[PDB]
Structures are given as C-alpha cells and as structure tokens.
Amino acid sequence: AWPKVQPEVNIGVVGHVDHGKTTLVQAITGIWTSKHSEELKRGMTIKLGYAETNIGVCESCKKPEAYVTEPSCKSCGSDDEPKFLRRISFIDAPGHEVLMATMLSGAALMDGAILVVAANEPFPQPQTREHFVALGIIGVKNLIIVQNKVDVVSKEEALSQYRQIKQFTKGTWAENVPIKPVSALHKINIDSLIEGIEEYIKTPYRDLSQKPVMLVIRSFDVNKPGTQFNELKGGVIGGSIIQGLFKVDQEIKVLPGLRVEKQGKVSYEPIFTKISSIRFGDEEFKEAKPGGLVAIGTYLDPSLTKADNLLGSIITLADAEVPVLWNIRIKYNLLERVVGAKEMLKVDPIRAKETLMLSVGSSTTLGIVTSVKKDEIEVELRRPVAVWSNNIRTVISRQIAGRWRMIGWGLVEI
Ligand SMILES: Nc1nc2c(ncn2[C@@H]2O[C@H](COP(=O)(O)OP(=O)(O)CP(=O)(O)O)[C@@H](O)[C@H]2O)c(=O)[nH]1
Ligand SMILES: [Mg+2]
Image (cartoon, rainbow, N blue to C red; front, side):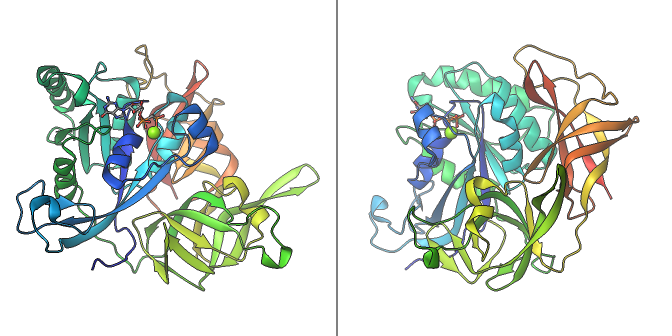
C-alpha cells in the first residue's frame, strides 16, 4: 500500500484569467480547488486554491504513461502496485488582474510553478507576463510552461504559439523551461505533464534545523452553526511552513498578531497559543514540515481566526525573536515597464509621499515613501510586518488607473 504522508512540495499554478489553471489542477488531482460560494457563483478563483495528490510510477511500463496519481498500474496492463514517489500539492492562484496581490502572496509558498498559457488566446497576455515576471523576481524558477486548451486548435496553431513562447523566454532565466501541451478539460497529455513535474520540479532540500516559520494564508474554525459552547472547537490557522518544522503541543505565536484598539489608537500585540492539532487535507499528523498547506489547530477563541482574519501573519515558536516593523528600509530595483498593464507603460521613479503596496511573505501592506534614494527607499507602513530573516524579498506595486500593478522588487534591510 501507499503511505499516508504530508505533501513534500508546493507547485504554484499561475497564468492569465480563464486560461485554465483550476481545471488543470482538477485534471491532475481530481479536485476542484474553488470552495468559496462567491468563487462558485462568479465562476472564478478568488482565494488561493489548494489540492494534493500522490505521484507514483509503474516501473515495468513505458513513460510517460507509467506515471500515475493513484496506486494502480492496470492502465498499462499490470496488477503490480506502482512505486510511490512523493505526495505533491498545488497552490492555485487567481488570474484576474485585480487579484495580482493574491498571486504574489501565493508565490511566497511555492517551491516551483506551472505557468498556464491558453493555446487559443494571443500570447503573451498581461497576466501571463505579470505572473511570469513575479515568479522570476520571487525566485520560483523551477518552472514548467503548460500550453492548455490545445483541444480547440490545430497542431500547427499550437506550434505557432509554441514558437512565440520560446521567443519570449529566450534571453531570460526561463530560456530552457519545458513547454507541455495539454487539454486540462478533456484530460489529454496529462501523463507527460506529470513526468515533467517529476523531472523539472524536484523536491528541494529542507534544512529542518532552521527556526520554524509558517506563512499564514487562511484562518477559520470547524464549528457548525448552533454549536454548544462547551463544544466550540478552537480557531484554526492555515498556511505553509517555509522553514523548519512544527509539532503538536508547541507553544507558538502569531505575528504581528492582534489589532488592539485603545480609544482610536491602534497597535499590534503578538497572539500566543499552543498547537492542539496538525492536519494536511484529510489526514492528521504529529508534525508539519515544508511542502503542502497545513491546518494548525489552536486553543484560540474562534472569533480571532474567523474569515481569514489572520491572512498575512506568520507563525513562529513563542520564544523566537522576530522584528515586527512599522517602518522598513528596502534595497530596491524597478522594472522598466508595467508588464501587467494592457497598454505599454513606463514605470515612473518612486516619489516621496507616494503610497506603495508591499508584498512580504504572505502579507500585503500599504505604506508611504518617507525617503527615496537610487538603491533604497524607506517606508512608513500602515500596519506592521513580521520580518523573520535578513534577506526577505518584497514585491512593490503602484496604483495605476485604479489598479495595483507590480512595478519593482527589493530586499527588506535589517
Ligand atoms: N476547451 C478547453 N477549455 C478549457 C480547458 N481548460 C479549461 N477550460 C475552460 O476555461 C474556462 C475557465 O477555466 P478555469 O480552469 O476556471 O480557468 P482559471 O484560469 O482557473 C480562471 P481564474 O483565472 O479566475 O482562476 C472554463 O470554461 C473551462 O472549462 C481546456 O483544456 N480546453
Ligand atoms: Mg482558477
């Protein structure tokens, strides 16, 4: 039988709106990531979606068909159990331009990524470019480009687009990134994509001695409405461990923590709690490592975790030393152009007093520029940000025509 383990690797799925990201995740895992009523109603991804699958291989069968996502080799005529390789999970990002920040948040949790490009739309669309560049900046460079929807165009049309994709990636870090043509909807050529995932998105080395840090993207409770008070389960916090590992019964804290109101005055205080449970998908565990999206059960009042209240927080062990900053200095670089805009636009230099959006880990925060130099800016933040390490990358966005657009990136200087 196959072991029940946590996913050991996170693969982002990104790309322009409606290019088929969520359907691709479904093709691979059997799961539809959109769980929220607003997502199902509007027919779009809004929150980061999530799905897991085991990956195995039928050792006595031809590849790529030999790769499977379930413990059966019958499709290649064998009754032998396939060899288990690893469990993997997908971080399914929204494609809508208005949701770029969510993509940025998700990118902090990715070990590698799939850029989905629809074969029946002109390449390169605005969020194809924006998501691509964001991946480059954040360092998610174990990339596979998936040409999706090949079922509705001829082979030669798909090939014309393939040539365009090679041209686009030529001279960039992605020059030799593989391109896999598939139909996510009708499940065509999926095995080849699985093989590509095994080949090009290998599980990275994890130094489990590092101080445990988790980036938070969800928070909620499992309390059915009309639940008795003596039955109210504690709040649950969801996210991905980026370094180290957590264990049941550990004393932890959420940073920056809770917003505190003292007659108009607002500060933040760390939330201290204890891990009462650890879950990945449907399975419970005693410890949680990088890879996968973990649900940490706590003793927190569920009101504190309700409705993703803690999105953007980090979690550490209670005694960790972590700067929680209301002002940050960033060593920055600007892009030449606003890549996510429909019409070509130059990036104006950063100006003092302008309000920028900073993406740091899973957090998204507005701040006012208080100092501008050639290589550095200083920013007064509207809400504080937890800075758990010395070389954290931030992505900088500017509001252009009412839309937040990525314009640059930097290193948060300690
Ligand atoms: N013909 C065809 N249609 C597809 C394929 N993959 C997805 N679609 C269709 O495209 C539409 C959008 O699919 P969806 O998977 O939700 O795309 P998405 O990129 O996740 C949308 P968002 O950017 O908001 O998250 C749906 O109608 C879906 O059935 C494909 O391989 N072939
Ligand atoms: Mg989607």
